[PDB]
Image (tube, rainbow, N blue to C red):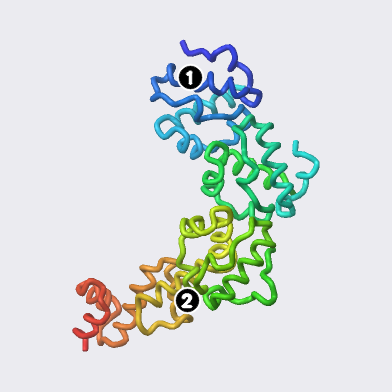
Amino acid sequence: SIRLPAHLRLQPIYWSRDDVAQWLKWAENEFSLRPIDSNTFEMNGKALLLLTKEDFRYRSPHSGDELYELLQHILKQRRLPAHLRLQPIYWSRDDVAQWLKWAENEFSLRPIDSNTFEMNGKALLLLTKEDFRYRSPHSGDVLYELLQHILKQRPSIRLPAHLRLQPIYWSRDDVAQWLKWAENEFSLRPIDSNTFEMNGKALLLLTKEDFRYRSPHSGDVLYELLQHILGGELQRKIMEVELSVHGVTHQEAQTALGATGGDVVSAIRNLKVDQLFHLSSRSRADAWRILEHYQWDLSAASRYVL
């Protein structure tokens, strides 16, 4: 009863952009799916096979997973340019520009402006898939999955000596000096020094959306670098703990945050329990229930115990 269209009886790796569009139209009618525009999968078969099931859901929230499983059953029933044969971590910005143009032709993607990835291979490896989608809404996830395949087929960053200090201790001038180095280390578009008029502690409280807002071309790189390379995430959690429990040391907050698995709420509540249990004559479990009775207020609970 069900039959593949004549064009689609070849292995999907050889499907053209017009083949996947025919596949989409045929899938909608055959399975009574909700309509999806043909401009939602602007790629050939080679790129389509790089997509994860999550990619299919992002593109088609109503039928993506159905389309993914359909493709897998068609499959089970069935290189790089000269400059890029290098490990991606060594790619220059011009290398990254060449990768974008090659992938665009190789996978029949919508045109990709070269200004969408003004960075080198070091910075490119820092981006999340969400950062790829932000920079390229039509092909970002394809480009991300392609990079993962290159890293798997193939088959370190030390800060400057003068800037070797934990971000939580950075002055406002250290923030500017970190920006100067980051532009050169990652071949970023130039950033004004007075875009982050704040110290390292304030810098750690900014979200990625705050970084994008200040630096539309390098914000996501700078955020990932700070939070997930230079130990900024753990230092951010220590501030949050120090802001919620009076009497906690940086070294004391670090111990509780480790015992909580990075959970700031569990760390604050266990530190509050630790202080009340020492001031009490009852067990640590009785301290939990007393704090819970006072809506987790250490001052009010300690007033009741004393």
Q: Is residue 301 above or below residue 86?
A: below
Instruction: Count the numbered circles shown.
Output: 2
Q: Earlier in the sequence, mark 2 or mark 1?
A: 1
Quarter of the image with the C terminus in it: bottom left
Q: Residue 171 is drawn in which quadrant?
A: bottom right
Disc 1 crowd, CA 10 A, few/some/many (<14, 14-19, 20+): some
Q: Is residue 221 above or below residue 71?
A: below
Q: From the viewer's perspective, is 147 left or right of 303?
A: right
Q: From the viewer's perspective, is 125 left or right of 135?
A: right
Q: Which mark is residue 254?
A: 2
The residue that appears at 33% across and 83% down in the rendered structure is 275
Q: Is residue 97 above or below residue 19?
A: below
- 94 or 265, which lies in front? 94
- 158 or 203, which lies in front? 203
Q: Which residue is mark 1?
A: 25
Q: Residue 149 is drawn in which quadrant?
A: top right
Q: Where does the image place residue 17, in percent across and percent down from the top left?
A: 60, 24
Q: Where does the image place residue 86, in percent across and percent down from the top left?
A: 77, 48
The residue that appears at 52% across and 67% down in the rendered structure is 196
Three-letter amino acid code of the residue under disc 2? Gln
Q: Residue 84 is drawn in which quadrant?
A: top right
- 77 or 139, which lies in front? 139
CA distance for labels 2 and 1: 56 Å
Q: Is residue 304 above or below residue 125?
A: below
- 234 or 131, which lies in front? 131
Q: Where does the image place residue 177, in percent across and percent down from the top left?
A: 62, 71
Q: Which mark is residue 123?
A: none
The residue that appears at 40% across and 31% down in the rendered structure is 62
Secondary structure type for disc 1:
helix
Three-letter amino acid code of the residue under disc 1? Lys
